[PDB]
Image 1: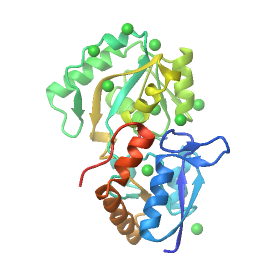
Image 2 (image 1 turned 90 degrees about the vertical axis):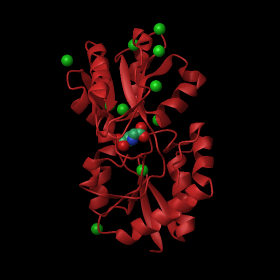
Image 3 (image 1 turned 120 degrees about the horizontal axis):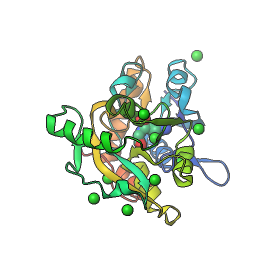
Length: 256
Ligand SMILES: NCCC[C@H](NCC(=O)O)C(=O)O
Ligand SMILES: [Cl-]
Ligand SMILES: [Cl-]
Ligand SMILES: [Cl-]
Ligand SMILES: [Cl-]
Ligand SMILES: [Cl-]
Ligand SMILES: [Cl-]
Ligand SMILES: [Cl-]
Ligand SMILES: [Cl-]
Ligand SMILES: [Cl-]
Ligand SMILES: [Cl-]
């Protein structure tokens, strides 16, 4: 490898989005360029809609995916992943005036890898509270997968982009959403969004998988080996931590 093409969504701030000049910016872009410098490879970022981001990788339209993509078991059946470059729990989003905010959280950190009757009881409590509540999620996400598999009795609307989800929540067309803390914290930290609040347990594992990684074709074992060495070095020297604070306003970097 001398040169690779990396796909990103271009509409998932602060991971990947467009600046005032329409240039691709974000945590994914800065990290991607940093990892490619360590691998001594020419880096080109391209914009790709979330819908066909995985089949365009397997079809050879580009060489990698850096688009806030969770290393989830369903995706591992189709593509390979690098080592996680970011770890993030998942939580719920609603309006600041919502009665949903007064709900008691019995389990602050909820792992989904081996759901106990206690963990299931907490999941069922939230499922029953979310009955009658209109939920909105971006289509093709682990957020949609969680709602369909874990909370099927909850009415959900799916969207092309996360920006349309946020728009409809602020407009009052939906009552709640679900995304990672890495997306929801910088969003709710904005003075623009003081009318929006995070709530409920912070969930990890299960269908959400084990962090955010680089999507690579399964046959490209050498490119994965290069990315894994570059990510381990970027984590060790504190580059991931620095970019996490810069873009997310907190440290979401993994530990060695
Ligand atoms: N359109 C990007 C959504 C990415 C999503 N990752 C969760 C998240 O980082 O909020 C997923 O893996 O499904
Ligand atoms: Cl966004
Ligand atoms: Cl081809
Ligand atoms: Cl990614
Ligand atoms: Cl309230
Ligand atoms: Cl509370
Ligand atoms: Cl979503
Ligand atoms: Cl329903
Ligand atoms: Cl939409
Ligand atoms: Cl609401
Ligand atoms: Cl929370």
